[PDB]
Image (cartoon, rainbow over all chains, first blue to last red; front, side, top):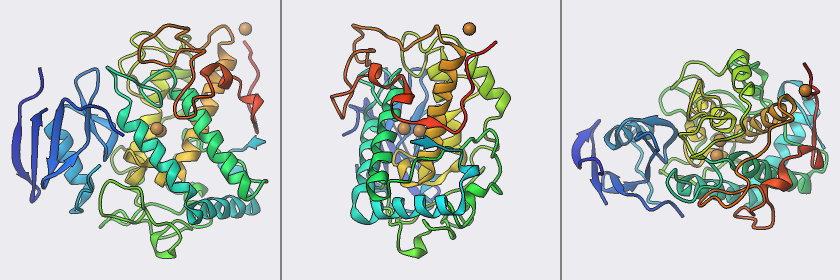
Length: 78
Length: 278
Ligand SMILES: [Cu+2]
Ligand SMILES: [Cu+2]
Ligand SMILES: [Cu+2]
């Protein structure tokens, strides 16, 4: 069963998650309306293409880690 | 071909390596290595097809990927080979690796931008083209997101693991491959990516030339593990869904198998690699 959806403004940016050249995601995340590729690991943790080697517990935590990494930069679609 | 510890390169070897990397960038060849890597890291999944990462073929796949890159460098300057970064030994920002004559140092605090060395954006010689966000400059934050690189004692604990890999052959596995990769245990390879920060922490991590030096040392640790465990070999050995078995070919090349890449000495040697011993 996929995680719940979420929607919040985090460090001034809108982050959203929802159940649904890259894998076939069962969950989608967006940063200011631009999709952020995210992936679930076997133990239930998550990573994203801007923090791929550093598992975090949830897709919202991956979205927040992406906003922290981007330091204001627009995300580019994959 | 001898792969040497970065810490030991002469000033001429550093110059020639840098120039060859910058020429692969100028000609457009470099960026296609970044693109290939990003495609595999975004596609390899624990529950489906997995070849470059999170799987037993993590090690032979990166061995062949590094061979492709080294061969491209040697097409520019035949004297250049890939150096390796022993991050257990050269573990500070003061390492010569990070000097302005080699890779340049950490990024400035405001935006992570690397400000010195041959790959700094201000040179005009290192545009970040294959990327996941607007920023087009190399970034690093050495020691920013994790405080320490692995220590020799931690590396030795991973090298002592006898089984190459184990079912389910993914990021949940016990065994040497997944402990070296870092998804379980004290964490070697993934933690180094996190320690460098910047593009190195992302799927487009070959944007930082340190990628090659990190992977050349991961590759050397595979060779060391084989010398410690001459009785142990690549698994699985046939009929495994979604995983590259020993004699199966690997994408993207399609013409090479893990079996063809187990013995590095067919392609290169190291400056030093201890013999099997007790
Ligand atoms: Cu990789
Ligand atoms: Cu890597
Ligand atoms: Cu023996």
